[PDB]
Image 1 (cartoon, rainbow over the protein chains, first blue to last red):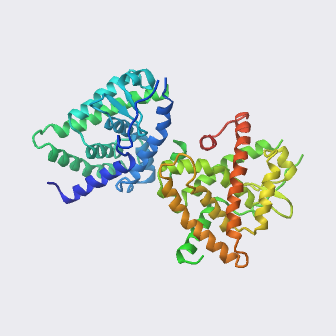
Image 2: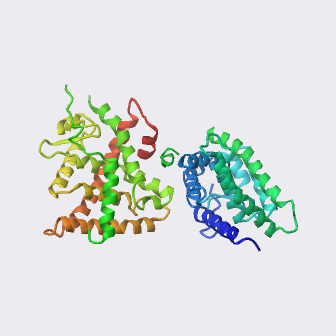
Image 3: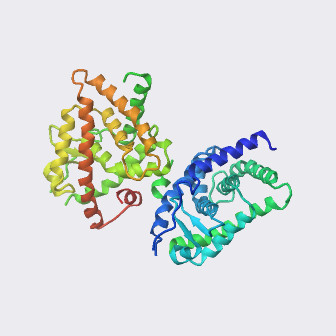
Length: 217
Length: 227
């Protein structure tokens, strides 16, 4: 249905996601018993560590200068974690899941450490489900976040943009193959990257209210 | 060590140690004159810092999750530093010497950072000199400490274990090369790891009291590990 290279790209990108963001409800989730943002903060360390590994597993990124890898990961990290979190949203049950299996309702999150943002997080995640976004799309779309040539202070921003160009074409074709009917689908998907930038800033604000990892040279 | 891979592995692990643990008596060691703890505690930062580098530079360790790297490094950091500090124990003069060259005596350390542990540290270090332990064997034991499947909270403890096994076999053959006469030396060297666990757990207890109840809590890499 699609180029041979591209299908190679999808699989490598998917596989990189899958290896560093395993599937859920096999090794089931749990719904909590009882105000408890302790775990949420706990899982942050591991969550970021995994996004790093995601990049290690995708030569393209591995092609880039070590400085640029750090710069892009620094800038991308929270965006990709949010996208992952959205990825685990359960439409049926109106819940979100952490990599541990901890599963929480919107209201439980509002009261805990997710604030007034929680509604806007859920709306976004719901938006992706309307667009029938799949694991492959989540992965590639993250990689588009990672390899973004507008980050401040890159050594070779032009190189970064070059590396980004094939994933963009691949995403387009994959989306087209899943959605031959709807020519709007690709634009809609990328513009959720815009949503994610804006959402990311707001989420970061609430983080306030990686030095061992940074030692990667 | 037997296979060409093993001899290679020794060289790699040895090299990484040397790269992160420079030789001493050259940039010679010196004794100040008269208190000392601040001198000791500052040097902690580098000491930790180099162990991180040791991990950075080493076969296989890099292969595993970023998480597991972090988990193992936190877990193993004090054991490796104690082992390193033992390497520099001087048998004639009864001294332990630091990065800089600063060299000290058992009593000085008792007043210095070490306190009640100091006797048990020196006992241990004495024990390693008896077994005639060399730089390469020190480097292997550090990685073996590092690559340890038993540490709590690992993502893939089975892999960490599998990654450990060739280094163990390699250490064995190397020990066999150096000690054809006594075949129980490899067993003896392993049991020193069990000593170092116990020694390390006591070490941590002192670190917690001393650093927080400290004039200066710094710095940024150093905090994360001990925590």
